[PDB]
Image: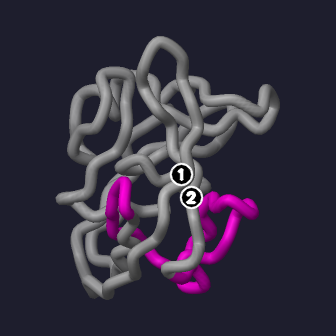
Amino acid sequence: EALTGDALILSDRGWLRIDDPTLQECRVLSYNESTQQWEWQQVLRWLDQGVRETWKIKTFQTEIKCTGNHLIRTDKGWIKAANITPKMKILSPEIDAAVKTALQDVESIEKLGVNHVYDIEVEHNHNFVANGLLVHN
């Protein structure tokens, strides 16, 4: 739902800060429920969120801090971020000759508290991947 200012989100170019040109002007990586595969969706509009508490979900492949109450995609499907535990795994995209899905293991979630938050909306799948972690929006 919301990502901290120092957070990074996948875009057409790749991993960049939540307030990068590619996130705000180029397509981003999402899990297309319709085609059951990774696809790029257009970033509708960059939105700020200012002061908001955040939880840092840490995984072996990546780590990021968001609202912590919004549901995010996991191996089993969408799950409340607060509910996520180290055991939980999240499917992430792999860039190469062909896009491939790979699960990452959650190390733990660490509270970051009140932070500056920013995020952008998407068109078709209504979802996007922040720092390799799929988040509903």
User: Taking 126 as reference, is 7 above or below it?
Assistant: below
The reply to whether the magenta stretch includes residue 130 is no
Q: Earlier in the sequence, mark 1 or mark 2?
A: 2
Q: Which residue shows up at 62% across the image and 32% down it?
A: 123
Q: Nearer the viewer, residue 90 or 44?
A: 90
Residue indicated by mark 1: 134
1 vs 2, front mark: 2
Q: Which residue shows up at 56% across the image and 30% down it?
A: 100
Local SS, label 1: strand
Disc 1 vs disc 2: Cβ atoms closer than 8 Å? Answer: yes
Q: Residues within 10 Å of mark 1 (few under 14, many from 20)?
A: many
Q: Position of residue 64 (x, y in %)?
A: 33, 63
Q: Position of residue 118 (x, y in %)?
A: 32, 56
Q: Which residues are magenta?
A: 60-85
Q: Position of residue 8 (x, y in %)?
A: 28, 49
Residue indicated by mark 2: 90
**Residue projecting furthest to the left:** 6
Please say whether residue 6 is visible from this viewpoint.
yes
**Residue projecting furthest to the right:** 34
User: Based on the displayed image, in which of its 4 quarters is residue 37 positioned?
Assistant: top right
Of helix, strand and loop, which mostly describes the magenta segment?
loop
Local SS, label 2: strand
Q: Residues within 10 Å of mark 2 (few under 14, many from 20)?
A: many
User: Taking 104 as reference, is 26 above or below it?
Assistant: above
Residue type highlighted by circle 1: Leu
Residue 43, which numbered label? none
Please say whether residue 69 is visible from this viewpoint.
no
Residue type highlighted by circle 2: Ile
User: Based on the displayed image, in which of its 4 quarters is residue 72 positioned?
Assistant: bottom right
